């Protein structure tokens, strides 16, 4: 008599655990799936930490609400059992074609016909994966950002095969779990946010790497010129420089030059950004 | 017994008049140069308006300070006389090689040896122009942003020939007139700000033009994802869509596609942005 109620999240890493917890915190019946009891033990630990963060950072989570959500999460390492009555499966497994390939082939078999599949993938297009699902009308991308409780966008992106009704149900699900749905109308690698942010960061990095200006100068220019609260390099520190290095080094020639610059000047010195307490800036 | 005192500004248009007025408002002896008495009459009008804006918008300009600055400005349509005792000449004539060519050839002849030349050019590199000056050690770019009293960056950019001492004097001049000096270390087309902003706006325009997302969605993504106060399309309205159209239409293929989109959907409807009270948004 209702739409989405049972949600299974595949994967319990940094992203999967936030998605699962956010979804649980907002009243849905969540099953967290992962490969064995060791991974499930680690997931419980991530969930306990998230409960703690919520109770301090998230409206309505104080006074035990976060723990009630925590205690209501079901853990499973049996995929068939994990998705047996799922209305929606959010897939957040590692960023591997082979690995998502075999998941979706099984998932398509194991899940009841009603089940909507959503990928959180940041490197693979729903078109790259749709064929394995066996239900193209019920497959799309639902893409979250790290720290979902605060950076609460959910970028919704299907294929030409996606059922509009399914798309709208995911949009309504996104809102129901407290996200701002960012509705894309066609596929686009990097969705919206990454599509906008990478060009800005690539531009700043080129200015640095080509010796045009120092980071402080580039950042103050951006803050003053656009009113933005943080400039590109402050943003690089937040992203994480190990992450920025990985991304840059499989990119274009100017980008790979920046990767080498980060590697020599930051990564090799243990200056990784916000995480270590120092990157381009000292915190 | 001092550095820069006499400043001549070449050109009295939107940019030249702001530069001249800002410089006058901060205590320097300013001569505004333009081609005839008709242009000089229009300059006086721009200065009167600027005085009015300052008295309402700029610290210290109330109670007649803006008018004292206004009344102290010298007007000239005789280049030789305009620069006879100039310590610094800020060139803000139209964006034309021929036109800047002949100005600099004359200027190099007419100005005393002491005179520093600074170009405000947004389309020409100081390297494009240095040969005409006859004083490469004293030529650089000093680049302002529209509404200099509020968007108060001054991007300083010389050539390999620029005297470091001259560069630092211009940096100190920039600060003395209330600007934040943005110090570039090597030439770069678009300096710093435009180098960062254009890639962001090109990315947003591609998302719009390729039908990925609507403007509202693209903007909220940027605001939420980076904390910036305005997204790309809000920024396009501020830039001015006629301006964005002109820039885009002499750019790359995706950019020219955006130009056509603006032309059909906005320019042709008199929706030019902030100026007309409606662009991508209604004001």
Image (cartoon, coloured by chain):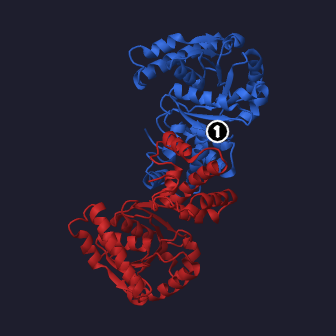
Chain colours: A blue, B red
> Where is mark 1, residue-wise?
A246
Q: Residue at x 59, y 11 (%)?
A: A74
**Residue B53 placement (x, y as % from top left):** 32, 65
Q: Is residue B277 left or right of residue A197?
A: left
Furthest-left residue in view? B63
Q: Nearer the viewer, residue A167 or B118?
A: A167
Q: Nearer the viewer, residue B30 or A194?
A: A194
Q: Nearer the viewer, residue A147 or B85?
A: A147
Q: Residue at x 24, y 74 (%)?
A: B68
Q: Is residue A164 visible?
A: yes
**Residue A1 placement (x, y as % from top left):** 60, 15
Q: Is residue A172 left or right of residue A122?
A: left
Which image quarter: residue B87? Answer: bottom left
On-image quarter of the N terminus of chain B? bottom left
Above or below for B91 versus A140: below
Which image quarter: residue A122? Answer: top right
Give the letter of the chain under mark 1.
A
Above or below for A271 versus B188: above
- Mark 1 crowd level (few <14, some 14–19, many ≥20, 10 Å Cα): few
**Residue A264 placement (x, y as % from top left):** 59, 44
Q: Nearer the viewer, residue A252 or B148?
A: B148
Q: Is residue B87 visible?
A: no
Q: Residue at x 45, y 22 (%)?
A: A54
**Residue A191 placement (x, y as % from top left):** 63, 40
Count of numbered circles on the image = 1
On-image quarter of the C terminus of chain B? bottom left
SS class, disc 1: helix
């Amino acid at each position: 008599m209702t739409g989405i109620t049972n949600v299974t999240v595949l994967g319990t890493g940094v992203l999967g655990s936030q998605i699962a917890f956010q979804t649980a915190f907002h009243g849905f019946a969540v099953t967290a799936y992962d490969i064995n009891t060791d991974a499930l033990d680690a997931a419980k630990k991530r969930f306990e930490g998230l409960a703690a963060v919520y109770e301090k950072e998230v409206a309505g989570a104080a006074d035990g609400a976060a723990q009630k959500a925590l205690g209501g999460i079901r853990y499973s390492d049996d995929l068939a059992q994990a998705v047996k009555d799922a209305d929606l499966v959010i897939e957040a497994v590692p960023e591997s074609l082979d690995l998502k390939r075999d998941i979706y082939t099984k998932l398509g078999e194991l899940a009841p016909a009603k089940t909507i599949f959503a990928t959180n993938s940041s490197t693979l297009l729903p078109s790259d994966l749709v064929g394995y699902t066996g239900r193209g009308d019920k497959f799309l991308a639902l893409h979250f950002a790290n720290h979902v409780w605060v950076n609460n966008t959910a970028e919704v992106m299907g294929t030409t095969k996606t059922d509009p009704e399914v798309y709208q149900q995911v949009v309504e699900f996104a809102s129901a779990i407290g996200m701002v749905p960012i509705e894309l109308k066609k596929e686009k690698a990097g969705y919206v946010l990454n599509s906008l942010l990478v060009p800005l960061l690539d531009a700043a990095a080129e200015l640095l790497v080509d010796g045009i200006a120092d980071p402080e100068t580039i950042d103050k220019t951006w803050r003053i010129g656009t009113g933005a609260p943080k400039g590109p390099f402050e943003i690089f520190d937040i992203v994480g420089l190990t992450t920025a290095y990985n991304i840059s080094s499989v990119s274009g020639p100017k980008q790979r030059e920046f990767a080498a610059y980060l590697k020599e000047n930051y990564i090799d010195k243990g200056k990784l950004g916000l995480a270590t307490g120092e990157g381009f800036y000292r915190y």
